Structures are given as structure tokens and as C-alpha cells.
Length: 103
Length: 60
Length: 299
Length: 65
Image 1 (cartoon, one colour):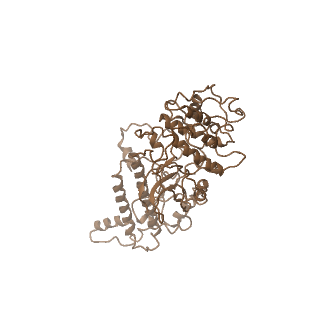
Image 2 (cartoon, rainbow over the protein chains, first blue to last red):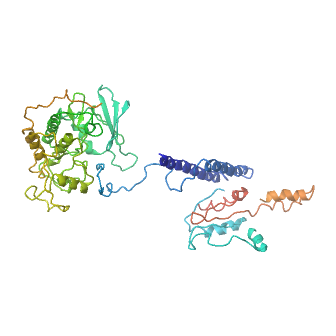
Image 3 (cartoon, rainbow over the protein chains, first blue to last red):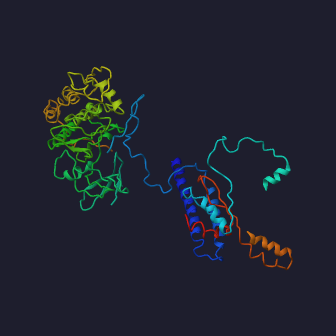
């Protein structure tokens, strides 16, 4: 349960980094669409809102490991191959039980 | 700082001539991540710096 | 209308929710499937003949059926509710004891398999828990998630199926052909579990299960089960003799040994079926079975 | 930026602007460059200033992404 909360917290932090990355794209798209010199103060305050957002994120985290997971967490690809299950169980002392096979 | 991405890598020579054609000047900075060989990126060197005529030119 | 939650399963989660119109309690078994993908199979027809053909066939030893609905993703099953099963009698809970009540279990189990074999239907999903019990004590089956309509010839089909604890000797080697002995193998295995109240065949995969079965029953020789070396997928083991069956089980009469030996036969062509098993000397004696009222129920 | 150093020059003259010819010129070359990082090519980010990015969209982004 502790490792499950750590892996789930990585997706929560990864989503905030993607929104912060996409926020700079929206500022560059509208940087010259409606700006003819007087509109230049908003870009200076853009990094100020991005710096304070990173300061409020680096503190409430116990330094998560660098992983490459999906922040949205959807139907991830496994192998889609007839891999069956374990490596033929392979006994050693007392046998247990293995789940049955399904289509 | 608003970071961008890479445009097919090959597109690069045409950008160096369009910026200087107008009026702004470019200045490619430091840092890299390709072609490594000397172990890592900190090698071996004593931190005891000397010669003030080189340290002042280094920080500049 | 969700009511209460029970447990999980192999590929379907059991839900105790009261359905509409019909006032009977329905145990919905939702099968986890897909719908997000484009060219996705979605629903599997391995249970299509279960929720469409069971309404026509009526039998007391066979589970019932009301309706059926779904849409690829969530396929909610509509089946009658059952009290307890059989695994709770042996596993964990050891307080519930059945003194000479096992005769009523095999009597109502062979009648259910005989009715399915008459309509050319095999229950290729035998495991020590499908024998569901209701309030009246009527022994009924669980689900038909691996049923198939067979005929006179026997061709190649699926392999490495069925619970690994109860596996036929011809199915572990990967034989292409099979027959009635597939469903008649676990009949004696369930009977062997209710006697000593312990797992009779505690094996692992297909390789470990061959060791436990052969060291207790024996190795099929040429006089016993012919046609063995012709199969490609074959392994050579030790010359296992054969442990008798009248000394392993303590509470076992003389008439009980006449049925256990015929069920554990390694020859599918010579293995006893359901009609010849009900006409033996075990189901025609003085200790008559109980109808179901005197049968105890778990807590 | 050149607009910051201009205010320091006006205070040094003590009530007096530096003519006015070089005041309108303080709008040509800016601070721009490229940085090589994990992208294995170029990552476009320079300085925390803002006038160094506004006057650039009408040249390179207009002809190629």
C-alpha cells in the first residue's frame, strides 16, 4: 500500500509538469496575436506564476524516483502475446496452486 | 523561460541565417547530452584554485 | 440496483444485487471485458450458449437461468442465488462435519453430468467449488463458461485448460483427442476430497501434476492404457506401480471402492461413465442418502 | 535590457537627457540563444527577461514549426 501511494503520487506530479509545460505553449501562441508593444507585462509575470508553482511542488514530495509512466493512466500495453503465466511453476518443496487458463 | 522542441533535427542551418538577417543576434549556450566517453562529466581536478588573473577572467 | 457484495472469481466478480420484476435474488457475475479498443473481440462466446440455451433445458441437478443482457463491455449475468458451495466444507472451516452424507453428493452430481452428455454437452470446467448448494440442499452446478457441443468424432481443441488440481491424465500430456473421461476424472477426485478432508492431488503446473498422480495411482502401461508413446508431447518418468485405494481412505466401505477404482482408470475408452456408475453396488444398499433436509449448512 | 541602463544614465547627467539620438537605437540586438540538453539537439530558452522573445515570432516560427 505504501508503494502504491508512491507510484500514484508520481502520476499526480507528472500531470502538473505537463500542464506547466503546456502553459508556456499557450503563452507563446498568444504572445503576438494581440500584442503591438504595450502588451509585454503579461510575459514577465508568466514565469513568476511558473516559479511559484514549482516551489509549491518540490516541497510536498519525498523525492520521487525518475520513472517513465503515464500520468493519465489508461489501457497501457503489456505484450498481447500468448505468454501463458509462470515458467511452468517449477516445484521445489510443497506445491501450492496456480490460476487456470482463460481465452 | 518558455522552452521549445526539435524540428526534425536537420532543420538548423536555415535558422542561423534568418535571425541575423533582421537585427537580433543568437548566442548558443552550453550543456550537452551526446557523444560521451571520458567516464562522466566531472573527471579529476583539484578544487584549490590559484592565479587571480585567471579566476577573474574565468568568472567573466 | 446494487444490494450486497460477495467475492471475486477467476474471470467474473460475483455481485449479490436484486434484479427487477423477478423477486428472486440474482447473483450477477460481471465478466471483466474490453470496449475502449476499436477492433476488439469484447464479449467472448464461451458463455453464449449458457445464457441462451439453459432456458430450454430443465433439470433439477442443473443451475437455472432467467434472462440475459449486456453490451460488449459489462455483461451482467442473471442467475439464481445459491447459499454456500463445497470448498468451505473442506477448506478452512472444519467444524461442519457430514457423517455418511457424501453418498448424496455423488448421486446428484452424476445425474447432472448424465443430462448434459445426453444433449452432447461437456462441462470442461471442473474444480472443487462449482457444486453450489441452496437452502433446500439441492446440489447444482455453477457456470458453463467452458461448455462445448461435441459429437461422435474427437478432434483437436484447446489445451492447458481446467483447474490444475483436477486434471485428467490424458489432458496433461497434451493429447489432441479426448472423450467422456474428461468429465469423469474429477468425479472421483471430489469424492476423494470429502473423505479425508484434504487435497488429494496437491500439484502445481502440468509437470508437477504428473508426479503426484503417477506416484499415487500409477503409470499407464501397455495393458492398461494403450497408445502412449505415439503422442509427440511425451515425457519419460519412473515405473510407478500403484498404491491401493482401500488403505488411504479411513472411512470407506467395500461398496465405495467399486466406484473409485472405475473413475481413476487411465483408459478413457474403458473408463466408466454416468449410466453404469449409477447402476453399481454403491448406490443400491441399506444406508440411503439424505434428500437434503438433514444436510448441515455452514455458518 | 537596454531600458534599465538608460535610467542610470539620465540620473548621472543630473537633470538632462542624453540628447535623444541613441535613445531610439536601444531596440536592436537582444539576448537570444540555444541550449543543448536532453532533447539531443536544441532547447530554445535563454534568459528570464521578456523583451528578448517578443521580437522573434515574425521570422522563424512563421516559416517553419
